[PDB]
């Protein structure tokens, strides 16, 4: 039931074997011959055309890679509930400054 | 300022490679007139003209990373540039599977570990279309 020399020697020999296989393969000048849900994603899009129209586009994504990246943003944006917020902050700063100026007028 | 030099590898057909090699090792400026390189605005297509004879070229991506290493004493070597592209002369087509050395052949297919979960750009385009829209309806689907 070795817990000491057996493990150490086994690791050492596997190390020498891999080192020696890599050296040989790499220095070879031999020529080498040239050789979960199963569910797709479909999106419906509603847009307005020039003049007056309301066409709807149904687009199906069968690439599971595109799927993963697409959904992950929605799930994030669904939990994410901004230029508008920055504008609101600017309005807040303006109001605060006006209030401070009113305070200065009251003091003087 | 200093701009890092951009080195790539040029692969020629073997007879044209022998003429270009003889003209390089000769060292005259006669080679300058003989060998020209025209790169097309595709970015992955060209002509290499050896002795005014046009050859069709493709700039391909190499699977490994090479590095040019210069030396003055042949004991200490200084890295000068990274090479990753080759203008072979005679997208998926612009990717080279083999490496330059003989042991590295079919490296991308066999000696490269592949880990997987363009696509990101397509997802960004889809998000932009959803934004330009009004109502979006989504369902993970089944066979249909």
Image (tube, coloured by chain):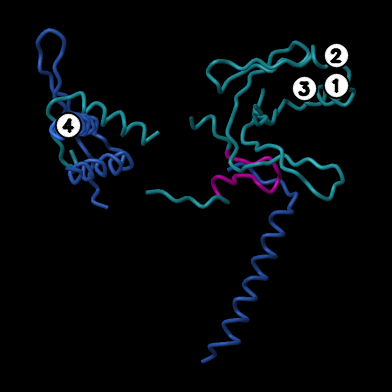
Q: Is there CB contact under 8 Å for labels 1 and 4?
A: no
The chain carrying label 3 is B
| Residue at the extreme bottom of the image, as rendered | A1
Q: Secondary structure at mark 4?
A: loop
Name the residue tied to disc 3.
Answer: B16
Relative placement, left or right, of B116 versus A56 is right
Find residue B26 and report its horizontal and vertical position in percent: 90, 23
- Give the mark nearest the N terminus, 2 or 3: 3
Measure the alpha-carbon separation of dots 3 and 1.
11 Å
Q: Residue at x 84, y 24 (%)?
A: B24
Q: For mark 2, what is the residue?
A: B30
**Residue B30: percent from left, percent from top:** 85, 14
* Residue depth check, mark 1 versus mark 4: number of the one nearer the observer: 4
Q: Are marks 2 and 1 on the same chain?
A: yes
Q: Which of the 4 image quarters holds residue A100? A: top left
Q: Under tag 1, what secondary structure?
A: helix
Q: Which residue is mark 1?
A: B23
Identify the image quadrant of residue B143: top left
Q: Colour of chain A?
A: blue
Magenta stretch bounds: B97-110
Where on the picture, by quarter, is residue B37?
Answer: top right
Q: Residue at 48% of width from left, 50% of height from top? A: B114
Magenta segment includes A1: no
Q: Which mark is residue A108?
A: 4
Marks 2 and 1 sit apart, C-alpha to C-alpha, by 8 Å
Reading the chain from its start, which is encountered first: label 3 or label 1? Answer: 3
């Amino acid at each position: 039931r070795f817990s000491v020399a057996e493990h150490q020697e086994r690791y050492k020999e596997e190390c020498q074997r891999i080192f020696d296989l890599q050296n040989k393969v790499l220095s070879s000048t031999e020529v080498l011959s040239t050789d979960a849900t199963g569910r797709c994603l479909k999106i419906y899009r509603t847009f307005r055309d020039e003049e007056g129209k309301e066409y709807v586009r149904c687009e199906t994504v069968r690439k599971p890679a595109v799927i993963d990246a697409y959904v992950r943003i929605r799930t994030t944006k669904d939990e994410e509930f901004h230029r508008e917020e920055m504008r609101k902050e600017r309005r807040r700063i303006q109001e605060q400054l006006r209030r401070l100026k009113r305070n200065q007028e009251k003091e003087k | 300022p200093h701009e890092l030099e951009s080195q790539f590898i040029l692969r020629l057909p073997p007879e044209y490679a022998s003429t270009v090699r003889r003209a390089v090792q000769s060292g005259h400026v006669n080679l300058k007139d003989r060998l020209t390189i025209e790169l097309h605005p595709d970015g992955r297509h060209g002509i290499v003209r050896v002795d005014r004879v046009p050859l069709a070229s493709k700039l391909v991506d190499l699977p490994c990373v090479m590095e040019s290493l210069k030396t003055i004493d042949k004991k200490t070597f200084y890295k000068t540039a990274d090479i990753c592209q080759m203008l072979v002369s005679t997208e998926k087509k612009f990717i080279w599977n083999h490496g330059i050395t003989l042991p590295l052949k079919n490296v991308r297919k066999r000696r490269f570990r592949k880990t997987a979960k363009d696509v990101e750009k397509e997802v960004k385009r889809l998000l932009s279309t959803d934004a330009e829209a009004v109502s979006t309806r989504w369902e993970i689907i089944a066979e249909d």
